[PDB]
Image (cartoon, rainbow, N blue to C red):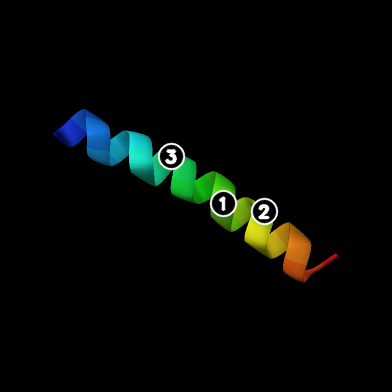
Amino acid sequence: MDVFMKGLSKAKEGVVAAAEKTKQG
């Protein structure tokens, strides 16, 4: 499940990226 965790975390970074970009514009 390590890979799955990395996959989720990788997606999270993108959602965070979106969250920051959206909350800053």
**How far separated are the C-alphas under marks 3 and 1?**
9 Å
Q: Position of residue 1 (x, y in %)?
A: 14, 34
Q: Which is closer to the viewer, label 3 or label 1?
A: 1
Residue drawn where x is 46% and y is 49% of the image? 12
Q: Position of residue 2 (x, y in %)?
A: 17, 35
Tag 1: amino acid: Val
Residue drawn where x is 74% and y is 70% of the image? 23
SS at badge 1: helix
Tag 2: amino acid: Ala
Evaluate if marks 1 and 2 touch, with contact meaning CB atoms under 8 Å apart.
yes
Give the number of callouts: 3
Task: Give the quarter of the image for residue 6.
Answer: top left
**How far separated are the C-alphas under marks 1 and 2?**
5 Å
SS at badge 3: helix
- Disc number at residue 10? 3
Task: Give the quarter of the image for residue 24.
Answer: bottom right
Q: Position of residue 20 (x, y in %)?
A: 68, 63
Tag 3: amino acid: Lys
In the picture, measured across the screen, residue 15 lies left or right of residue 20, that is left
